[PDB]
Image (cartoon, rainbow, N blue to C red; front, side, top):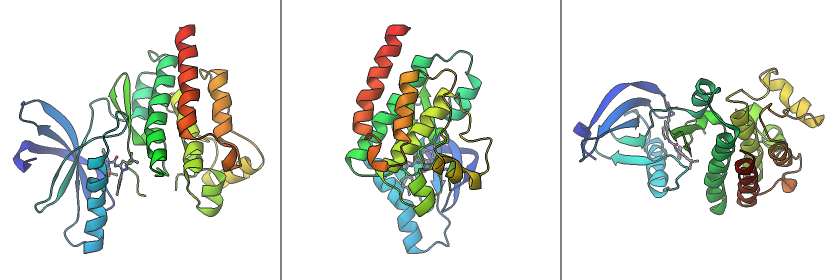
Length: 256
Ligand SMILES: Cc1ccc(-n2nc(C(C)(C)C)cc2NC(=O)Nc2cccc3cc(C(=O)NC(C)C)[nH]c23)cc1
């Protein structure tokens, strides 16, 4: 990927190692691809420059249909990591904007797609630690992609073991994933929006849970409740949750 083939438009935000730019990449075909161009401050340590590159190293190896895509890497100074963006933006903003036209089967489709992405990460014992609708992009009205645009706390999405002891496992991600589904079925509503972060653990310890979103099928809410078991061992694996969500999707397809 050549630097002249990438035009920068505006600052997307500040990453951990430097600014992230929203740009456009013109390929060999001439078609314009929306991209996020991640940069690293010059004054960083070699250790910090290495940690910056690890995203390019890992992301190059990821090719899952429901995971964000790496477009390329420009190693020559200033080093850029180019990731694909889509014009439909974040899922949270997309859900809010299309709340009146989106059908429940589509919300179950998105839930299943993220579950498939997470079942793959589970296969390689990798933990996301920040499963939330803000970390999901809309590739098309029928395709969502999981990413990680956060800085390595998201209290309102975290399992009790993550809040209490900073323990993060695949089991804790399963909890976060059900919170992500609650956001999808609620059309982008923030979980526990009515609480402060300090109040969350007290409510979970007492046995209180996020209520069923109006449009959420009872079977899907039961699955959400199993992911929110205080005991991490009693939550399903993403691998089996794919089977569970595929059954829910087929029942919703049969209803619609
Ligand atoms: C070090 C490290 C960091 C992250 C990851 N990692 N792991 C995964 C899973 C495998 C899905 C968990 C995905 C990712 N990376 C991305 O999704 N990158 C990405 C893609 C598209 C756009 C943006 C914007 C930013 C950004 O920094 N925006 C600031 C403005 C905050 N990042 C983007 C791996 C290693």
